[PDB]
Length: 148
Length: 148
Length: 148
Image 1 (cartoon, one colour):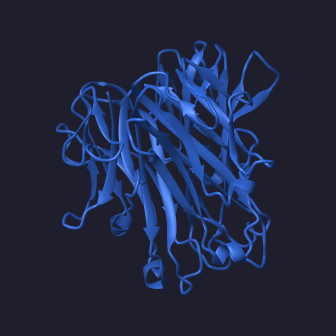
Image 2 (cartoon, helix red, strand yellow; image 1 turned 45 degrees about the vertical axis):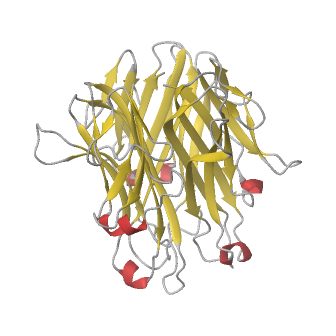
Image 3 (spheres, chains in turn yellow, cyan, orange; image 1 turned 90 degrees about the vertical axis):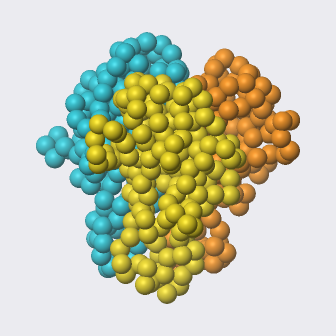
C-alpha cells in the first residue's frame, strides 16, 4: 500500500487539488485518491507525510493582519461527522521588514506513523489565505501515505 | 514494530517529556518508552523521526545573545561509550523586528533510516533555553520509530 | 534494502559529497553509492529523503541578490529523458537586517515514497552558491533511500 500525490491550487475550486496521474504520482495496494482525500484499504499502521511550498507576496496590508503558515492532515470518517487534526505544522511567515517587499518562499514538511482504520479518509488543511500561493513546478507540494 | 510518542515541556522535571499514553501515542512489536528514551527490541533497520513545535517570545533581552533552534536524536548503545547524534537540525530563531511584538512560531522535523542494535536507546536533544516554549497541542511535537 | 549517506562540502572540488562510511551511514540490500548518486537494485517503491544544513555569513550583496536555499533530489532514468525533480524545497535565506551580522542557520528536509526502476540513479541538487556553507558535522546533511 503506497501512494504519493502532487498538488496545486485550483482557480475554480478554492482548494489544493491532489492528483495521482501526474509527475511522480502513483497509487498501489489499495491506497487510492477519492475527492482530494486518501482512502485507507485496511486497519493498520501507515506513515503519512505532506509538503506544501509557498511563494508569499507578503507586504504591509497583508502582514499587519497576523497570518501563519499552517499545514495539517485531517482524518475523515463515516463514523464521525466533523474532522480530527492527525498532525499539523505551523510557522510564522514574512520574517522581514514590510515596505521593502519582495517575494518570501517557505516550505512545510511533516510525516508520522499512525494507527488508522479501514475506511478512514485523509485530507489536507492549509491556511486558506495562502492557498493562491502554493507552487507545483516539480513535486514542490505533495501528499503521500504508505502501509508500514 | 512501531512507536509514536507525543511530547510536551514538563515544568517540574524541566524536560521534553515524551509519553506513549496521550493523543495518538502508541507502542507496538517490542519498541517501548523507558525514561524518555525509545528502547530498540532487536538488531535491524529502523526509520527514526521527530518534530518539535515552538512558540517563541523572542523579546530583545532574550535576543542579541544568539540562541538557535536545535533538535537532535542521540543514540546510546551497549556497543560504545556514551552517545552519538543520529541526525540533527538547526535554525536561526527570532528573525522578525526586536522591539516589535508577536510570538514567533517555528516547527522542526527530521526523519531517516539507521542501522540499530538490540538494547539501543534513542533520546532527543533540544535547545534547553527553548524547552518552556515547546507546544504539545495534539501532536505538534512527536518522536517515533518503526522497523523497516 | 536501505542506505543512509552523510554529506559535506568538498573544498578541493566545489561539490556536496555523499559518504557511505562516516558517522551513522550504512548500505544494505543492493542500495549503493556510485559517484554522488544512489543506484536503485530492483524495481519497486522506495522512500527517498534528504536534509541539508547551512550556516551563512549572510552580508548585504547576497541579500539584495535575493538568493534562496533550494534542495532537490533528481532521478536519472533510461526510461525518461534527462534528470527529473523527484521533489524540491526552496527557502528564503538571510531574513534579518545586513550591517549587524551573526551567522544565519537553516535546514531543508524532504522525504517521500516513489516508484523507481532497476538502474535508476538518485542525486541531489543544492543552490551552488551555498555549497561552501553546508555543515558536515553530526547528521546535519544526509541522503537516504529504503525499499518499502
